[PDB]
Length: 63
DNA sequence: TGTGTCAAGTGGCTGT
DNA sequence: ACAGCCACTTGACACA
Image (cartoon, rainbow, N blue to C red):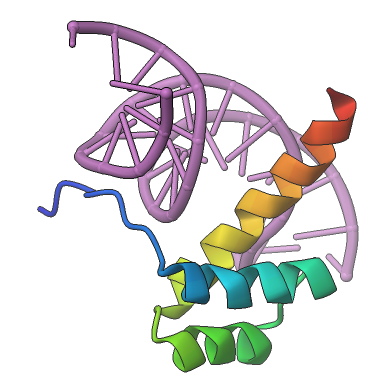
């Protein structure tokens, strides 16, 4: 029972995720498990940072 | 001296 | 029957 320690990605990992979202809003299963394998994060760690920029970018303009 | 942040987790609806 | 975002909160932690 791991206690969900927070987990951050190196700023270089994050740069490649900022990369795939700033270039594309929806990642397919092969595309997205490749960013996960270049930087060495797992696939669900990439898919989740993706769900986070779509609610935060749109919600910024509703503000 | 405590929140807001971060990423996950949660929780709830509609297509195909 | 199928499968999973889309938006709210928690659940640890970086901010100052």
